[PDB]
Length: 633
Image (cartoon, rainbow, N blue to C red; front, top):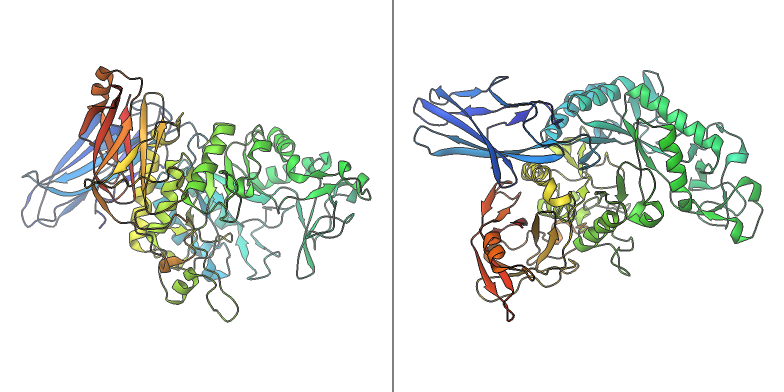
């Protein structure tokens, strides 16, 4: 159900002083030689800023792709740090619409305000190696990501070792990879970094912050190691903190407060980033632990100990000072520690979230779409930033007899696809709340069917399910939406205590739990920005609210399609004249197939409550998975 317009831009992202060069393809799919017209309307939210247009006389079945200069949005035409929509209609000489497609355009200083982050990793077909022979596949994936406006790339497992992350050699072995013995060809990584940069995006190098590999000579004296306070998973009290598998040490850890380690790892990362052309550091840690310095390793006094997480903010501030031209972030697994970390000098906030983490809502697991929203909100409240969420989908898991341990593993045995709507709902839940779901991946992997991958597990190169063509196309639609409406979703936009409600035409209230922890509802809530309100409608009709879909297709995640819904929104404190004005300026947009980020005007009536306060009664024509109502106010 995709179009053949092949709408493409020269870059993924633009500075305000940079022209947008667009190319589009006009197809005469008719039996008559005639003028075919491409009309590309440039919208800023509901406002049509420009109409672009070009017509070409084409013989039957003839196509023409526009050349450089033919469709252009000149420099200094668009306000900075904003998203726009290009709404394209191809028409014949009778004004019949032959095909339609929409594309967002992102104008921004850099990726920090509205991060749209994808991963890049080695190829499962080639022992998870990163190889020059796979560049053509990577470049096809990267072209698709460019046209999805991705502004940043997480280079996963491209490093040699934690203390020598990207040396100047042609190839290296990743010796810590004991399961497949992956290799890296450095020219391949450099070519991927150069290609990312051609699009305007940045390249982030993933590496641990405190680690060294256990089978390499220590890069510093034991005075700089960190020690366990209590006997546990990382070894005995008074011994170096060690990550082991099957009684074999894999990594030892340094004290974040060690100045020698701070200087060592910052300088090592600077050299590695300069070797590869990287733009910053995607940090990680093995997990939190109560620890002692070397000087205190023999103490049993808890007041002499500290949690690693209580020194991460200081360590990151030191890294930022030592890496001033580089971007920096640190995964905070399950978002446990935003309160501790809120003042740290990270450029973006990144959390890998798991359903077994404790929810930001309180004492429940982080397993539902509403728990993802709550974490996003918690980060915005603490830092003012939009949370990048790693929330890997389905994660099929097996035992040794390949017995499935979950329903997604049953799908794997059936050579099935990812459950498209499950992935889209998680992406929707996170973006509607003001975050970004880091889900898309360039992995040169055959199960991605020529498109882009979807992250399924912590080891990003693994793709056990197929990405259907439908999911590839709908992922593209959703990325255009998250770009085009970024200013409505995450630019000084906060929760609204006004409680919208959603009804069918025949007397049912479909909004039942505004926290989004129960399914079988139209999850409905509002947000407030500077001159507007939004109402998010996430369709959970007839489906559960768990975001991960570990069941795969054993638990259907296509919600029951709705039509002709009514949404109410109270305007208490607003005059009738202002309400009437607002009612003529209610719009809806959706990334689902019926609109593909197009915006429509909604019929709306102003009624009053018992006290004469205005209430909007908004007619919503359709809800597939995700609608956003935009109320100018």
